[PDB]
Image (tube, rainbow over all chains, first blue to last red):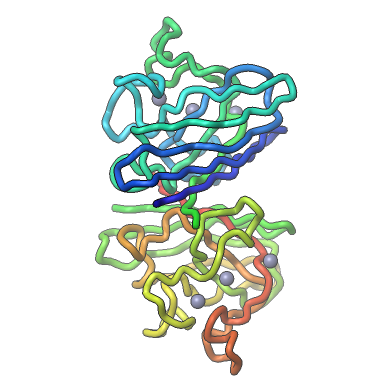
Length: 153
Length: 153
Ligand SMILES: [Zn+2]
Ligand SMILES: [Zn+2]
Ligand SMILES: [Zn+2]
Ligand SMILES: [Zn+2]
Ligand SMILES: [Zn+2]
Ligand SMILES: [Zn+2]
């Protein structure tokens, strides 16, 4: 049983707390928590490569992509490791997060510990937006909040 | 080869950037950067076990101590992995950090990535304070600032 945690903070109203739990060494990871201060709708939700917060989220680098794939959604075969799709905020601006993912890991080459979790301004189009950028980033706009994923008890 | 970074922030105005570089996994880690807003003198400087800053620096847990040793200074055989000693602030409140350490690592079970770096109120007594706490925490007082250590480019 391995656990991780991430506090999401930014320059504006967006903040949250995200927990990760992996029961078995190469098993699925449960992702749960809450993010507040959002606009109602979909917000892109990504693990970026670097746990570099020195310039806030500006510093986090590209999507975590150890297997040199293209951008997609979490249910796609063709995805980056860090492609966790979207979270959904309600009209109160709160997103209750509840994800199970079998590509991210809390150990080894797919490990996300020490990387940056980012929530975005816009929806991630999951590689289905109709331009070149869709296949790289998903066109999810500004980085509203982020944090470094840390080992938890 | 390996690099890591950490932004230290407080509930007060203690701000720092700390870099880690390890040229090979069997080598020392160079720790460099700066911390401002400190009182003149010595401030304890630790890697705490958990990269959990959900409730600020308290969430970070005890000293990182994978080998089940007692507290010391970084030059001691008997130390925790996370025992990096003290940093020194000048009368301008700035500590310029320059450390080489052979016990922390950026890989393996002495790896510090995803853990919390903390700078303290007071001096760590390095195990040489004359009470039982000295052998556990070093009596360095409150956690002034902290952040989660992340993978860098
Ligand atoms: Zn992103
Ligand atoms: Zn992606
Ligand atoms: Zn942004
Ligand atoms: Zn400490
Ligand atoms: Zn210690
Ligand atoms: Zn404190």
